Structures are given as C-alpha cells and as structure tokens.
Amino acid sequence: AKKVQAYVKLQVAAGMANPSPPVGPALGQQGVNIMEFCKAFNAKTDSIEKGLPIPVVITVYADRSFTFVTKTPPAAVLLKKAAGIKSGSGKPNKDKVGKISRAQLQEIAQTKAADMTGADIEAMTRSIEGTARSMGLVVED
Amino acid sequence: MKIINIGVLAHVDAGKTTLTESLLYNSGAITELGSVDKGTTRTDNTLLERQRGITIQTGITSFQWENTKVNIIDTPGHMDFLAEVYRSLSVLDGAILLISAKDGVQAQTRILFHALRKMGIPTIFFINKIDQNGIDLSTVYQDIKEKLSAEIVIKQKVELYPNVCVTNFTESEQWDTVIEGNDDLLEKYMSGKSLEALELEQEESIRFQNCSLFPLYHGSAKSNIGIDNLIEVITNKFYSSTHRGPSELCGNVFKIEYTKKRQRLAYIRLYSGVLHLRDSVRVSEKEKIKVTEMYTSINGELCKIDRAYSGEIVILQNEFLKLNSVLGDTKLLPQRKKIENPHPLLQTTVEPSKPEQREMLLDALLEISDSDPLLRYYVDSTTHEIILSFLGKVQMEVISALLQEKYHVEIEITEPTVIYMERPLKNAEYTIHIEVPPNPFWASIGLSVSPLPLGSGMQYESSVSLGYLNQSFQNAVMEGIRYGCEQGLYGWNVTDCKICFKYGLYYSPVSTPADFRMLAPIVLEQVLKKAGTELLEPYLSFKIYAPQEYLSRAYNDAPKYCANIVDTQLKNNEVILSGEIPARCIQEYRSDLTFFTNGRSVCLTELKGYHVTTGEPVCQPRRPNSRIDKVRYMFNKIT
Amino acid sequence: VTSYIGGEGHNLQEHSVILIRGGRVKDLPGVRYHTVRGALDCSGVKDRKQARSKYGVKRPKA
Amino acid sequence: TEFDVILKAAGANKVAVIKAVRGATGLGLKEAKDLVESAPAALKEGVSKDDAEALKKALEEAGAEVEVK
C-alpha cells in the first residue's frame, strides 16, 4: 500500500469522452497519454449510467499505464435529477431553495456505502443528509 | 588533389573558432605572426568584429597540412543569427564541433549538432579547453554520450595534469561497437580472437562515411597539447575532394559580404570542373557573366589565383550574384534548412535619425540584404515604419554596430504598429438625409450598420429595391463604405462590419455615382459614432517547448503573461504546452523562455483570431484619413 | 520635379528610386513629367493588355 | 516471475547471440563478446518469464542452446 505519489480525484462528467476544456492539462500533467482518459475511461462508464461525474484513482506509474479503482460519485451532483432542481446553495438559510425527505435520501445512502466508511448505516445516513443542509436544503424528517 | 573544408561548430560561445586560429600556426609558417591572445588576427576580416569579442559572421582562411588542402571557417556559433552558420554547411561536408568542458556540450550547441545530422555529412567532437579546472575528464565526457544520443566513442583519452596523451588509447576490448553494425565487421566479430586495430579502421572508415559517430578528440588548444596531432586526423578522417576537371564546370554561391574595399565579392565553391580566368560562364540570370577577378581567401592575406581547383571555394567579384545561384547550371544537391524555426523573431522598429539623413539609412537596409541571406524587411505600415525580419538580442547589436561603421545612421524602435481592429459596439439608426439640407452630393442613402460576431469581418447587402438601388451606381455605395472601413473615429481599422443599406432617395438630374460614394463614407463615420467605439487586439496562439523540470517555472510566467492557460502534453523529457497570448505582449514572451528555460526554451506561433478586446482607455492610433476628396466636410459633421 | 504617376495604382512608397520621362500632363499645375512604369523598382500596372509597351508590362505567358 | 535466463552456449550462430545479449541490457559489444567467452553464464536474473521466453525463443532461431532457471 504505497502512499502518495501522483494520484488525483478530478474529472468532470463521465459521458464527456476525452475532456479538454474542463480538465485538459491536469490529467496530462504526468507522463500518461491524453488517449488514456477516453478509450479506457469509458470502459467502466458503459457499465452504468453515462454523464455522472465519478471520481477515480489515478496512481500513475513509470510503466506507461496505471492501476485504477472506480469509486462513488459525489452527493452534490446526485442532488439534481433526484432532487428535481439543478441548483443548490448560494442562499442557504436565507430562503428554502428546495426540500426532499429522509425516507428517500436514506434509501440512496447504502448505494454509496461501498465507498463510505461507517460502522452502521444509520451513522452514514445523517453524514450524507447533513451535506444537503450545507446546500440550504431542509430534509423532511 | 584538394581536400574537404573543415567544420567550425563552436556552439554556445565555445571559442572553437578561436582554436581554428591555432591551426594556422601548425600549418605555418614559413612567415607568419603565429596569432595572439584575444583579437588578434585569425582572419578577423571586417572591422568591429574582434573588438566585439566575436565575429559578426562566419569567416574563412587558407590552410594546408599533410600535403593536402585544409580550408575551414568559424565560428557562427555566437547568438543569435545562427541560421547564417547553416549556410556554411554547404561550404564543406566536414564538421568539427567543439563541445564545452562545462557539464558536457552546451544545449545551444545541441541544436547545431542535431542540425548536422540533417546535413548528411560527418562530424566529430573535440575536447576544447581540456587544460582547465573542473573539466569532465571522466564525468563530463559521459554527458556527450547522453547528448549525442548515439554510440560515438573517443579514439583516445587522458587525464591531466601536465600530460596530454592522445595516441596512447584507445577503446580497448569494449571499443569497436560501431564495427559491430557494419555487415563486414560484424562477421569478423563472430570469428573471435584478437585482431589489429588497423583492421577495424577499415570498417570504421565505412561507418565514418555515414557519419555514424563523432571522431574522438581531446586537449585544449591553449595548452598546446594534442591541438596539432588531432589536426592530422582531420586530414585523414576528412573525405577526399571530388577532383575531376572533366567539365562542364558547375557550382553554386555560398556566402558574400560587402567589404568597404570590395565593394562586392560573392564567393562560391566549384561543385565540378574549373573556370578559366577572364572567361564567360553560365549563371541563374540566363546571361553571360565572366569572372573578371578571383582569389583564394588565404588566412594570412588575400591572394589571387589564375583558376580555382575543382572542389575549391574562393571569393570572386561580379556585377550581380543572387544567393544560392547555380554556377552551371546546375548543381544537383539536396538538404534541409531553416532560420532557427522563426518567420519573425520579434520585429523591432529602427527609424533613422534626422528628417533626411534617416532616408539614406534605408538604403543601408538594402545592404543588410547583401550580407546574411536570412534577412527581410518591408514598409507595410502607412508610416513606413521599419520591420526587420532579424531576431535575437545580441544579433541585433551587429546590425546596430554595422550602422555605426558601414553607414552613418541609427534608430531605436520596438513597439511596432498596434494592429488594432476596432469594431462598433452596437447597431443604431442613421441616415444621410434627403434633398439639400445639406451638403454635396445631393445623393444620399441611410446606412444602418449592425453588430457582428468577432472575426466575421466586413459585410453589406443591397436592401434597397430596384431601380432605386441602382444596378451600377449602387456599387459605389459599397466601394465608398469600404473607404470608411480604413479607420474608425479613433483611427482604428474597421472590423465586424454589417452595414445593411436601406433608404436612398436621390434626384436624377443632378445625381452622380460619385455623389452616392461620397455621402456613403459619411454614413459610416456617423453610424460609427453611435457605435461608441470597441477596441480589440489579436491573440494568436503560441505553443512552446520547455524542459519538464523547468516546466513548473513556466507557470510563473503565465501570471505575468496576458495569455490564458491552454492544453499541452509532455513528450518524454521534453515538454510543451499550447498557449495563446496577445501579439502586443507576445514579442516579450520570447525573452521569458530565454531566461526561465535556461537555454532550453523554444516556442512558435502565428497570428489568428481577430477577437480580443482589452483595456484600458481604448487608445487609438492616429490618423485617418487624409489626401482624399471632400474630407474637410466631415469636420462639419462633428458640429 | 514632381512627375505624375501613370497607370492604375503603384507599389511606390516614400523613397523607391524610379526612372523619369518627360512630357507635360496638361492638367496638374507644377507637373511637366511622367514616371516610367515598368522601370527599376517601379513595377508595372497589374493585368495590362492593350498598349502594354507603355508602363513596361510584358507579353503574357498564356 | 523471476526465472533465470542462463545461456549454456552461443551455439553455431554465436554472432546472432551477440545482438540478443546486447539488446538484453544495453551492454557493449566488446563486453557482450567477452561474456560469450564467459559462458556458461546467466543473461539475466529476476526477469519475468514472459520476457525471458522471448529472448530464449529468439535463441532457438539462432540454433543456440539455453538453460531456463
């Protein structure tokens, strides 16, 4: 389990094959080819829904290519299609931009549990639901 | 008979051209001063050369050794205007670059060393300044292997100390890997057993023709140890001269300089045959052009000769001589060339001093075209501002120093034309009126310019219906609108035009097609006043290559540069990135890669994208316009 | 002298040494000469056809 | 993946072995020839069996012997 070397968690939507206006040089900052982030980046994207920004480990090695393990998309972009509104924070406590409820957000929580580190599902419920409070959203308990 | 010309690739101010002056003493005398420290003769030639510490252009001197001719010239490696040294590669297939003793061969010489591969002619490294402290007697020589990027090995090596052994080597046991590549030498390696090194010199002689590896060399010329015996190898290692005399004679020009005592002399090597003195010959102009005089360029002094040998190179006077002109025709040789990869290395103004004496300086600018061929200039600007194609910092000093001696004029300029392309900010109603409120001509039309996306250029359409649009007179309206696109109210050139003309009442008995052309220009200066002005500047992209270790230092230059970041990809140890910065500040970008790059910097770009726009104040360059009919009436429109 | 520039346009600017022929223009005051188009750096008028011996234009290649 | 790549002999095509060994470590042709006189000797150690199988199979085209380890 080697520590830090060159890996980063930054790329936009998974449906955007071979990004450049977003990431651009940042992924090409190492010796890895720009072609590596579309021909292989989509090899796992095809398994699930396209267009969802999913972070992935990029542990570059001297031997041309690199190992990688896909993770879980952030809950911020998850609060769009499942929340209706594409907006978020900006005006948190000053006004209610939207609201969902605990019956639904807790139902999505265990799908992300494969990446989350929690002793119990209830402990991982409010840590995700508490991120929507930063958005000004008011969960319906 | 003859002999190939020796090289002189003293890259990064290696002073290997100053080692050539020591070779003239070894070929001496029987009567010569023997050279001296500093300047110093050594075929210095033009004035203000050795006083500058380095020659303004590559020279030449006569010499011989081993019962063979051994012409050579140096250095051309200073700066800065190194493309001129590329023209000397045609003077001789030989090479003899002097790698520096400080950290291996200088990186600027690696560009001239990689250019030697494109020549297709052999070259050899030499241990210049071997008698000095910090020299890489066993460490820096390994750096020439990493920089050579091949398998060249020295034929001898020593470490000192007062000793300067050279023949004691070399490359025992392991040496001879180049023979392994030979189809014949690789078969002798299969037989095994020891063999004489002269036997491997035949297979190395085949590989020397392909220039597969630089011949070995060592010993600084200042120590006077190995600077003469190593010169004997140039006689045997150099390729034999292509003697013939069978005819018909052929050749091509190589270089020329406007000597004050000349006044002209376009020297050129004889590719084949020989030219009798005072006899006509063929040329590229397709006319007769006898050589009335010609002489060999002796290192100690010029010397006439009744006829050049075959394969020789010597100056000769003529009434005219285009650069690279066939002495046949025609020469049949092919090679790659470039002016250091730069169509324009930061143009700078050089307006001459004095209201009249500056004009005679313009004719001296034609004399710069008689010198180095990598030079160009044109008065494209309406002010006739100078725009020389020469680039580099120290290289400009020779062009400025030349003005203080060869002529009597000088100038200082650098900003250049701003290249503004102002566009209207928004579309607005306008009209030239009707009848005679009013001023000439009585014909009028209501121009209605509108905004357009950047880079779309000028546009117009004939909205008026016939016959009032005029099948013939309506075209003057467009030709007259174009007169108003030569400059806006701030004098900036018209951009993003979209003048869709509409109303155009006119009286027939007094109307003329010039009358509509005249009122049309006023519709463009009135409708441009409603635009409120919109200054914009070009922002062409400028890709550049920098070493990855210094690549992090190139991001600091980004905040100072007006350009925004762009995509780039690494390429092994080399690195590059796609920039895009405005041309007003792009000329200063070259200074940034010469410093932060440490000499490894390299870049290239070209103008593109009319869109830009930047602050502040929206300054404009006067003035537009004058020397045109009815121009004083546009002043009445202001009030 | 202030010789008139004949033909349609010219590449001349500021200096540009040119040959000068005689003959008054019978129109511009102060002018009694004509510029020799097609001589020296004074290039001839583009795409001339009839009367091309004047202005120095050459016989077309096509 | 650390099989030996010992070379028992250069074989009847010992000249061809000098190229397969020279490209096996970037060693010089002079040392690559004295190593032929140093036979038997390992050409490499710790290398993956996928790599040494290519350098060994190339020795089969030269008629030379090899000894995997």
Image: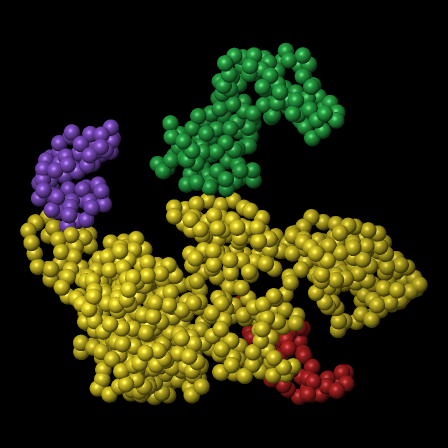
Chain colours: A green, B yellow, C red, D purple
Looking at the rendering, which quadrant does residue B314 occupy? bottom left
Q: For residue D19, say whether it is visible.
A: yes
Q: Note whether B349 is above or below B573 in the view shown.
A: below
Q: Is residue B520 left or right of residue B92?
A: right
Name which residue lies at 84% across and 52% down.
B429
Instruction: Give the image location of residue D6, x and y in percent.
Output: 14, 34
Q: Residue furthest left?
A: B193
The answer to whether B213 is drawn above or below residue B69 in the figure is above
Horizontally, residue B299 falls left or right of residue A132, namely: left
Front-most of residues B270 and A102: A102
Q: What's the residue at 29%, 77% (across, down)? A: B21
Q: Does the image show residue C52? A: no
Relative side of C54 to A19, left or right: right
Q: Residue at x 42, y 59 (%)?
A: B599
From the image, which quarter does the N terminus of chain B lie in? bottom left
Image quadrant in which the C terminus of chain B is located: bottom right
The answer to which of C52 and C40 lies nearer the viewer is C40
Front-most of B534 and B54? B54
Q: Position of residue B301 (x, y in %)?
A: 32, 86
Find residue B613 and report its horizontal and vertical position in percent.
67, 53
**B311 or B403, which is in the foreground?**
B403
Q: Position of residue B112 (x, y in %)?
A: 36, 62
Q: Residue at x 13, y 36 (%)?
A: D7
